[PDB]
Image (cartoon, coloured by chain):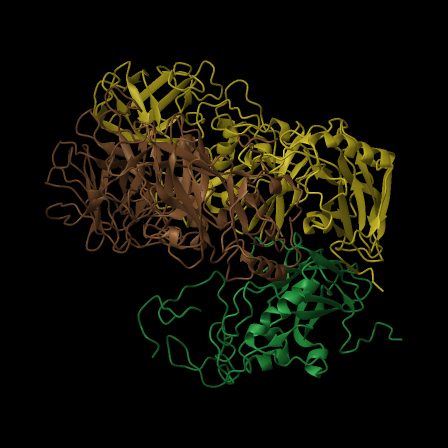
Chain colours: A yellow, B green, C brown
Amino acid sequence: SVPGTTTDGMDPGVVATTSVVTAENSSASIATAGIGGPPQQVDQQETWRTNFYYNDVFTWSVADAPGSILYTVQHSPQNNPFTAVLSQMYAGWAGGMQFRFIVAGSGVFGGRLVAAVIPPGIEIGPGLEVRQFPHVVIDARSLEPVTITMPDLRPNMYHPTGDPGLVPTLVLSVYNNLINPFGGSTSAIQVTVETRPSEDFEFVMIRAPSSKTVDSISPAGLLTTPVLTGVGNDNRWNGQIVGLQPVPGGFSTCNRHWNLNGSTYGWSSPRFADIDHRRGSASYPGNNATNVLQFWYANAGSAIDNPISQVAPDGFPDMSFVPFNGPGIPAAGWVGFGAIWNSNSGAPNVTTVQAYELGFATGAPGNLQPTTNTSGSQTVAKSIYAVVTGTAQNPAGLFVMASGVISTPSANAITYTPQPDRIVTTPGTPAAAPVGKNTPIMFASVVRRTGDVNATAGSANGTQYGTGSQPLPVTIGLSLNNYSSALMPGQFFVWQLTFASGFMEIGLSVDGYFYAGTGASTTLIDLTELIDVRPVGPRPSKSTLVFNLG
Amino acid sequence: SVPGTTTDGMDPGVVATTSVVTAENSSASIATAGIGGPPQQVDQQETWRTNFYYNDVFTWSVADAPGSILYTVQHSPQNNPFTAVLSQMYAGWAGGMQFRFIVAGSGVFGGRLVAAVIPPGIEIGPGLEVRQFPHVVIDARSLEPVTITMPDLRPNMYHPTGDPGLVPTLVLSVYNNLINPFGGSTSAIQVTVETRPSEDFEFVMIRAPSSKTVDSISPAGLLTTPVLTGVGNDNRWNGQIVGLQPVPGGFSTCNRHWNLNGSTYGWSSPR
Amino acid sequence: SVPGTTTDGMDPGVVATTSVVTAENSSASIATAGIGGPPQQVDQQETWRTNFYYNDVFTWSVADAPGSILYTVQHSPQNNPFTAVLSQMYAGWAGGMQFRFIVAGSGVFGGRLVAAVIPPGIEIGPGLEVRQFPHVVIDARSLEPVTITMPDLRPNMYHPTGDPGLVPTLVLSVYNNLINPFGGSTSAIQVTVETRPSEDFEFVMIRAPSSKTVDSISPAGLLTTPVLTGVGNDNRWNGQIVGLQPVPGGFSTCNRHWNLNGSTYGWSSPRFADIDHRRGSASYPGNNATNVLQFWYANAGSAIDNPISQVAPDGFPDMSFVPFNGPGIPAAGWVGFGAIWNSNSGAPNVTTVQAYELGFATGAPGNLQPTTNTSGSQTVAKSIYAVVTGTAQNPAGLFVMASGVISTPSANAITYTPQPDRIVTTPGTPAAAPVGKNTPIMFASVVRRTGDVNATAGSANGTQYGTGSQPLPVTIGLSLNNYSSALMPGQFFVWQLTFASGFMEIGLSVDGYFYAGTGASTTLIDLTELIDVRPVGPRPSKSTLVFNLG
């Protein structure tokens, strides 16, 4: 006898068929994937083919209404961890994949789940009625696993590895409300999804692995475990990422931000080199030239140095200029050490070296006001400390070092200084907006300031944070590879961030912005107990990313 | 007609073989380990090798997330009591070892465990994912015991007792969260691990009692009963230890402090 | 009929046996790799198993003496491009591999090659007599391919994927001098090596690919094509790598340099953050405090801030201090913008902001002399331009920004400024020395200066170069992973850099230094027409790396 309480790795449990799984589909799938040649990696006795391996886990609570979606997977060789390795030596794939669900509940629970394979060409999200497709209904009291097969319903004769085309989507939604007849704090059970290729899965043509690599067919390898723990910086301050900042209002970052199409709207390369502009006018107030505040300005659009955009010099911060006058230190400003140099010889001036506040403004000879649009604006520098003399040369130049620190009027730290009310954006960049319970996030790094240059993380004076839209390895890999055929609009590419106590998901839209499903919470995420990052793949944007840190 | 509520000492229960237990692994283990001469203590009627005996017990809480480690042991003679007695009497070993798990829960509980055998070269830590190995899943409502045999996967021809080298590792983690539908104070059950050598386990060379090398006898002898309620002094002062106090936040002492690997970072020899 | 002039991909040509290939070795290899379980990926009709795929090409000239080694490969699943993909899902391997040699010569050429499989435990290099092993002799006039099989002569019962153990080595040396009876400029032919697994090759256990990944078993993925073209920086100046600098005398870099054991001797993390030191004495000369040169110094060894070494603060340059006085700009110095800050509050001073030269010196109150050893020395800063007033506080602090520029006394550029005569090294770091015709190389990046801040690559004023020991992605990946069981001492890990016109090899020693076989040439390599980088694996250090750029 074999009890139902212990299940083998190769045991499928009960096999739950659906009208979408037909012999005609299987025979047509084999017969027309044969245009790739003989099927490859089809040995039935291989260990990667015979066992089920983990794909996901999800929670089913009593508050989950009938029709609400709990699980959604897209047909891919990236669901299985071993067909994802084998796809790096083959140029195509076809066939189906089995999905084994193990429900972890007792015999006292009620409520049921429903499972349908959704054909390609149908939008996946809320309002998709899973119970009016051909479906299967699973109890909460299932002891044995329930494996359903996802066939290859494809309009192409095989899926190329780079662009697969249209694929089905397996949806597990709530059929009936899960009930606990006991009543109390214990109202949730868990369902584990595992996966294994079907008997008619195959790869079709071989190809050299030095062709389109793992970094060009999916953005799974961009956001790996050392990137988010201690190695990757951000794309604004070049500082070690120590957290995530949820932005419930939404923001819009243009500079050093790459979308999933391999394009940018900014004026900066994916690197932190210096800001060097030629022929911008420099000036200094009054008639006396001792301890004066050096000023520099140049119209946006006349920076003919960058092969990416003519708006601003490379590495210029996309922050509005905060106005200040006299010997008063401004609040929340990008300042960076630099100098004024004569354009005719390239020689920097001896005495005009200071920490210059860099930003975007509107009227440089008159009243200095901040701005966000680059149109009709100008890139404006002005030193925050005293400079002896000052170059009043009109064709003069400005050279400012790459990384920047925070201007703070006192020793005490302030909030994260690129707030969305002052981030400079060209006309045309799309904005990150909260979709469902998923709010956009930034990537906080500890950035020191001009009030305490000894201030580190956890300083008793107060810790200072600067935020970026993307990690630098993420936007470095996004500029080098194109992932248009990896995510439709209205979809996220989700990773899982396992922590020491909890676990929580982030997702990347086609715009390039990252999202965590935290709702309206503004509390910074610690990112210190982060142990593991793994990808799970394309998911709907209107499906809440999980977030529990307790 | 045993009802399943009472299990014999020799009864394994349901045998769950993942993908590592193969016949020709056993054949390539038995034939190869003849480099230690004739195999010793191989009599499959002796009671020390036919019965399951206690090794460890562990607690499965409702707060243990999926993927959390509950019970991991490297392949060793030390996972069995009588094999640990005989391992000081011999200088090499080979073969597998069965692990019988008995879950102490009623039929009202829910949640699953996952057990895999990890191959010898793999590093075991935070990044190891155990459900993406060939595994077996065990329910919290298991009445009969479940036996998972870890075979002897090895690149060496046998395992020296002082330097076994690369061994496989049985890893038992949480597959699904443990659920009590009542809630309340009861939030943890217990699993007892019994152990018994496999059909192909053996020793080879004899050697003098108490004489091996690396993997020095685990430091169970440096901390005994009197240390706390008798002799035994401190590092800064020479007084009896009257209590322990927990510091929230941590500390750092590097004067008379020696680490697992014998080394000090500082002055002041321990006297 | 099948002519010998056209050969199939699956055609082995003639099969050249050796006494090292025996039936007892094959049967023992199968019978004892069976302890891993059933053999995996052993389907004989698979396309990756049946075809030969490219491994290497090498040149055989008339100047190559009898006994000189032309080709050397180590037994590995990294020789084949498809067993290298399959090794990411398996925990072990065993069995042999075939090597197919196609000699490209006419029937007018003379001379012969010899081929032996060398057993493990034997040193590979010059003076290894291949003609006194069991061997096979191949003409220069061979029309059909010659395939010889490399058996698995192993003392382990299988090779684990991470550490394989002792493996054989296939050596192709010269048997007889290649002769052209014609005489002239055409004195070289080419031999192509291809590879295919043997019938008894296998993988033994499956494992999850999220285990020890491709970046931990071999350093092949560290030096990839975007790293050396336009993305990677260097570990000294954080600038885009535009070339390689051959150093025929040898050098020794300690700071921000990681070896293959995952260890460093430097005082810097693999990142370019700022230099922040507490309690170093600051001073300024004379009694007047206008336009004075600010000075700062602190003894090396009293920087209690770094969790890696107490020698110097994190990010401090390993360059000797070049002395200067008065209003004279020094030559070839690390200068970086910074300030002096009061240690009791962390507040930077308003007026002491300048471009400070940073270096290592010996006597700070007396005569400032340069130094290379860190022992008995001190980290010394001194501004290169005028600073109003100056903090004379003994417990004061220094904060200098991360990246540095060159100090140049005129507008004109100079040689690459971290010359090996001034690179600061702790006592204990090993030095890069020329082995054979292979000389160590650095990684030149265009670093701008204080004489022309508009100076870029190819400037009519003159281009300025700063060199580092390693690329930043290479030393970032070397700190995260340990490759002790990837290269024995006396070996290089070679990559191939294919250019538009030529192709040339670099190799990485266990010390962490890179080598190119260029002899005594000091000419900088252009690295602009670099199109492809691929790895080839462990090779002897006393075997000249190829170099032809024409």
Q: Is residue A72 above or below residue C208?
A: above
Expressed as whole percent of the image width and height from the top left, the position of residue C451 reads 22, 26
Number of marks in picture: 0
Q: In the rendering, at what x and y percent does residue C152 appear?
A: 53, 55
Residue C397 image position (x, y, % from top left) = 27, 46
Residue C490 in view, yes or no? yes
Image height check: is B225 above or below C23? below
Q: Quadrant of the N terminus of chain B?
A: bottom right
Residue B150 in which image quadrant: bottom right
Pick the front one: A311 or A85: A85
Q: Nearer the viewer, residue A525 or C341?
A: A525
Asked whether residue A463 is in view, the answer is no
Lateral position of residue C65 relative to residue C194, left or right: left
Task: Say whether residue A529 is left or right of residue C414.
Answer: right
Which quadrant: the C terminus of chain B?
Answer: bottom left
| Quadrant in the picture for residue B257 | bottom left
- Residue C353 percent coordinates (x, y): 26, 35
Asked where in the image residue A309 lies, by quadrant, the reply is top left
Q: Which residue in the rendered view is the most extreme toward the right?
A: B1
- The answer to whether A263 is drawn above or below residue B21 in the figure is above
Residue in the picture at 37% in, 69% down: B263
Vertical comparison of A386 with B97: above or below: above
Q: Nearer the viewer, residue C115 or C162?
A: C115
Name the one closer to the observer, C170 or A212.
Answer: C170
